[PDB]
Amino acid sequence: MYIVQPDPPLELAVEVKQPEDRKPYLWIKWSPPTLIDLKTGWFTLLYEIRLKPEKAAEWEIHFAGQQTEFKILSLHPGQKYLVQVRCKPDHGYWSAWSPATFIQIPSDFTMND
């Protein structure tokens, strides 16, 4: 029962979505770990996303759950954000982070046109 690190949610794709009607948001989506497929039985793989802008001294943790995509509404146009998501496989629980992804929120985030 040694805690090994098989596959974290890799291919962390971060996109800024600006809807015409809805509010502009950061759309974070990741790829589920290869093999296993924690779909059978009530043992689903939950994901947690932590993010914060450059001038943020503290991290904002947002637990997504079973869904493999998360949206951030509280964003500052024209600022750097750091994002991380990780899952907890049956034989490999986590207590630390690693995949720090750098995403730039465009100044065009707000429709100042």
Image (spheres, helix red, strand yellow):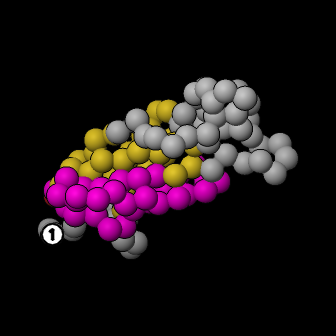
Q: Is residue 39 above or below residue 33?
A: below
Q: Is residue 27 above or below residue 23?
A: above
In the picture provided, is 79 more to the left or to the right than 100? left
Q: Is residue 47 above or below residue 77?
A: above
What residue span does the magenta drawing correspond to? Answer: 49-78
Q: Look at the numbered disc 1 and give the secondary structure of its residue.
A: loop
**Would you say residue 59 sits in the magenta stretch?**
yes
Between residues 107 and 20, which one lies in front from this camera angle? 107
Which picture quadrant has residue 74? bottom left
Residue 46 image position (x, y, % from top left): 63, 50
Q: Is residue 2 above or below residue 57?
A: above
In the picture provided, is 32 more to the left or to the right than 59? right
Between residues 91 and 84, which one lies in front from this camera angle? 91
Residue drawn at x 15%, y 69% is 112
In the picture provided, is 20 more to the left or to the right than 36? left
Residue, disc 1: 112
Residue drawn at x 53%, y 37% is 9
Would you say residue 42 is visible in this rendering?
yes
